Image 1 (cartoon, rainbow, N blue to C red):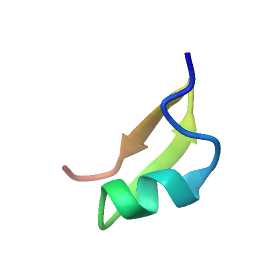
Image 2: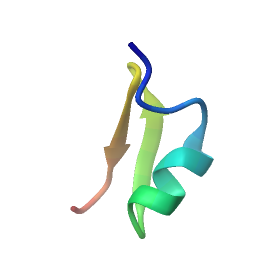
Image 3: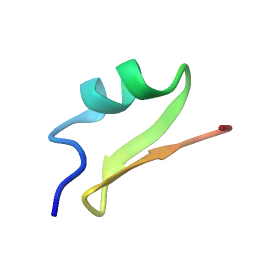
Length: 30
């Protein structure tokens, strides 16, 4: 269960991601 492969995935999801980590793309302020 990996929402993302890499920060890339979050970068489209979120203007300022934290990490693609824990199979869930963490966003720094969203």
